[PDB]
Image (cartoon, rainbow over all chains, first blue to last red; front, side, top):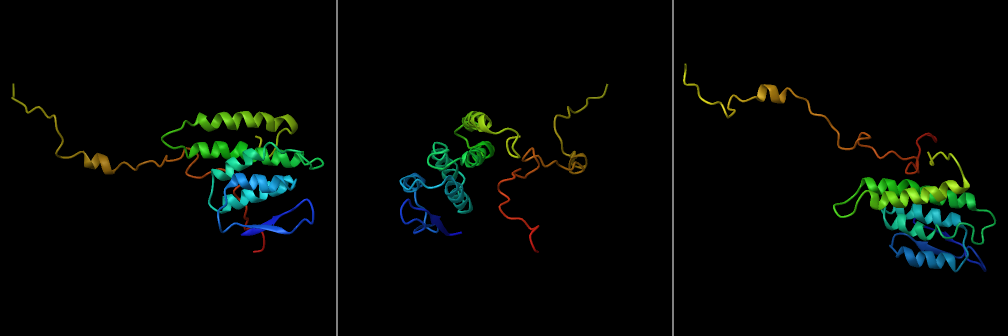
Length: 129
Length: 48
């Protein structure tokens, strides 16, 4: 919403990040991953950043969420394919709002390569095609 | 022969042939909409 929950390792369900302020997304990766937090929260705060009106830090913090597919998660690789299809769609979406400086391929390369790892685990998603 | 003016210029103008043309809208080739199944976080299909 404006503050959803980030679970801890010990005495979980205690800490919050209020989204009315804008923290940097890289320290978010940290404060999530010292807590071995489930991959679902990475999608949830990505959606929080997107509903906060962000398309680029939103799409680059999830690149740091591409590392932790099944880190301590007990088969949340379904959650990693959901993570990676978001970049496979929003790299190619942010390539359409291209600017004067980069190329379209400057995002299409990352979209196409990450899609290949997206199809390593799962085939013919409703977003793969 | 007649000494015709070289008609290198438009003053009639061609505006009858011009504003009769209705102009296409091709700003975005998929017709001005971002095509996405992820940004519908909301849905009106719920009540109501």
